[PDB]
Image: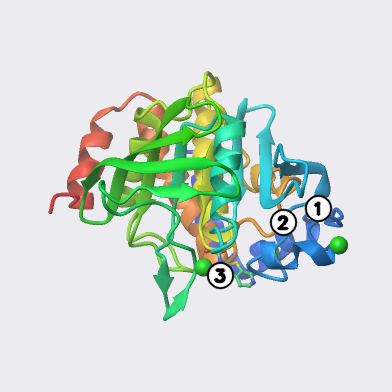
Amino acid sequence: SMEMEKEFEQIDKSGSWAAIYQDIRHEASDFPCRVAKLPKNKNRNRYRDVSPFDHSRIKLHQEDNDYINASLIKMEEAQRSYILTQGPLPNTCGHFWEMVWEQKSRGVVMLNRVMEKGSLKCAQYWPQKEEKEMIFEDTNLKLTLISEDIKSYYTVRQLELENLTTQETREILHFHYTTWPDFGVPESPASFLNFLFKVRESGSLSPEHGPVVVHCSAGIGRSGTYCLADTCLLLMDKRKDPSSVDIKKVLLEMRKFRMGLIQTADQLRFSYLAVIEGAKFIMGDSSVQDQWKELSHEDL
Ligand SMILES: O=C(O)C(=O)Nc1sc2c(c1C(=O)O)CCNC2
Ligand SMILES: [Cl-]
Ligand SMILES: [Cl-]
Ligand SMILES: [Cl-]
């Protein structure tokens, strides 16, 4: 059994998930967020306590106001980057797709629903009907729903994003997880890993593309959980060595680039479970992938 499994058992036995998680919060980086806190950006932030650090914020390529609440998580050893961002607001959907355009992203991973716990956690930023495309006048972009593949707990959409200035167009894949509760965890490691591997298999993480965009409502809790699991699996894979992966150190590295990644101790505990289970595929048992698809009951 792997060292992360032994660590997992000892933390479970001693009941120390809350203390381990608080240790991470105490040790996490603290960098300034001066642009995010400028008065003119107040209505560009969904949550007053969630801001991108200045050193890693994504800048929009426009001259009026380049601010978006979004961070580039640049994982050097893993050689994968992610853009983590908040669920766009009704006035920032144009900025969101501007950022997708300028950063050359091929995929968007959405881990939340538009309404959760009775509240609007994210704007309806993509078109729900092929024949009702959206136009973002402020950033001069057009967004059309091309097709969607609805499964029982996630939906994959094919979108066309057009730069109306140049009339160039790109296909964006939208991976929408619809049964992951806010401040909660997926239903099982299997359904989570099935979804995560759906993203991987799409090619959206290819280094020929810009960084994948990942968001939940705040871009930190569910987004941090997804990214930690994905990065740890990729590191294990590069080295073919589960024991070289220190999950808490990877999370602390990610938190150099955006605050608050992973919002509960149970989400941390879930990340361990997902990485431990996914290690079976990494280390050469491809049949677990079929097993996850079955256990996830994705068919409708
Ligand atoms: O969507 C997520 O997974 C996430 O981290 N959400 C977060 S983090 C966070 C909040 C929320 C929210 O959704 O209310 C409220 C304000 N404090 C921090
Ligand atoms: Cl200002
Ligand atoms: Cl909203
Ligand atoms: Cl935190």
Image quadrant in which the N terminus is located: top left
Q: Type of residue at label 1? A: Ser
Q: Are marks 1 and 2 in contact (CB under 8 Å)?
A: yes
Q: Secondary structure at mark 2?
A: loop
Q: Local crowd at mark 2 within 10 Å, few (<14), some, or many (≥20)?
A: many
Disc 3 Cβ-to-ligand 4 distance below 8 Å: no
Q: Position of residue 111 (x, y in %)?
A: 44, 55
Disc 1 Cβ-to-ligand 4 distance below 8 Å: no
| Residue depicted at x 71% and y 37% | 61
Residue occupied by mark 2: 259
Q: Position of residue 254 (x, y in %)?
A: 68, 44
| Residue depicted at x 46% and y 31% | 106
Q: Seen from this angle, which residue lies furthest bottom?
A: 118
Tag in front: 3 or 1:
1
Residue 119 drawn above or below residue 245: below
Residue 243 drawn above or below residue 17: above
Q: Secondary structure at mark 1?
A: loop
Between 32 and 230, which is closer to the camera in this rendering? 32
Residue occupied by mark 1: 29
| Residue depicted at x 12% and y 54% | 300
Q: Earlier in the sequence, mark 3 or mark 1?
A: 3
> Within the image, what quadrant is residue 17 found in?
bottom right
Q: In 3D space, how far apart are the residues under numbered discs 2 and 3 (Cα atoms)? A: 25 Å
Residue occupied by mark 3: 15
